[PDB]
Picture 1 (cartoon, rainbow, N blue to C red):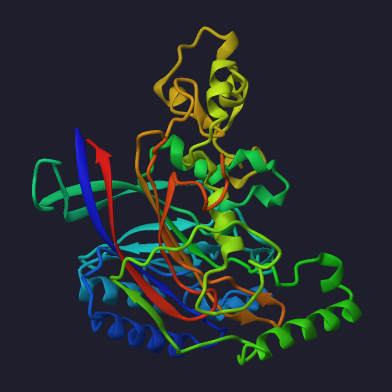
Picture 2 (picture 1 turned 90 degrees about the horizontal axis):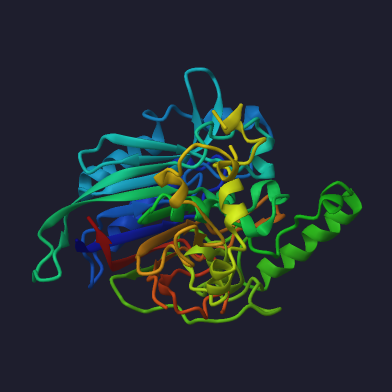
Length: 431
């Protein structure tokens, strides 16, 4: 049974700085106010915030982040999310620094339903270097999914209005979750996007604090005060030439509420990573994010992989998480040479978007991807890429970037202004 769903999706893009929680909260209500005053405004069903949306991101020591951590159901981020959800009767997802009853620290994203109750709390699974500075934990559950009840979003193809309720299978991935494990794992694993395709996720939500490549990341530069000081001056110039303060733009809102302006498909060159034109997306990063969702993209060569059975050993050998991940600190199994039968979960597994049953497992399906990435700058070394956006994978049948027409670019914010974007997203599911 095919079911046509319609969702109104709002993304908020912020430039939070450490120690400005209250100011950031005020700018959020200011942004939300303007949104509802948009000419083409419609009530969102879901609102998504960036990774560490109110607190800032670049904490260098545990004692520095302690003043901003909270329990999953208390504190400024939860209260903000609860109020938003109640005033808009929507789901609200926001990233915050979390502490549990055992005094353990996580990088987290909480989910609030329209009733204003917390229905979920996801924890970052793949950590980035910054998280290691304050003893952050890996999500012991690894990648997760959860249901989201939407009212008046669904309809049969025969019907003329969206007057049905639908439970979507959702997944949250926080920034580094999209990367290869520790940047050491093979690129072709595509852990998170594979997990989403395997579990038939329909709604993919990514709070992010993702870097523009102009940032300083070379480890020898950071630890050579001569090289580091020289590297910092380079970034200072870049921001000054844009007429912006070192921390980046705040309080000047770019709003794309209800329009259907799509983002232009563009290849990456030695200029798409330049930090310029703050109202334009970082297309180097946009192409890269799309690439990390390879298993959702049409790829011609999958027909050969399947006919020749080139990936059966990979599909069968594939584990749920990386062996050394916190997840196993659960089990395990060579089904090829055993007497155990092939379970359904094995026939759902994929590698490079191929399953045991078919060349391209996602073919003919739909899925929505919401990326909420922060903007701005921290420590005079780090430039976040902004470019929050909404995407649709259509499953319709060579290019590994935005040129590939199996993904639709429904809109993006600019690489460096606080703002919001709303889109009516239409897609189909099966029930």
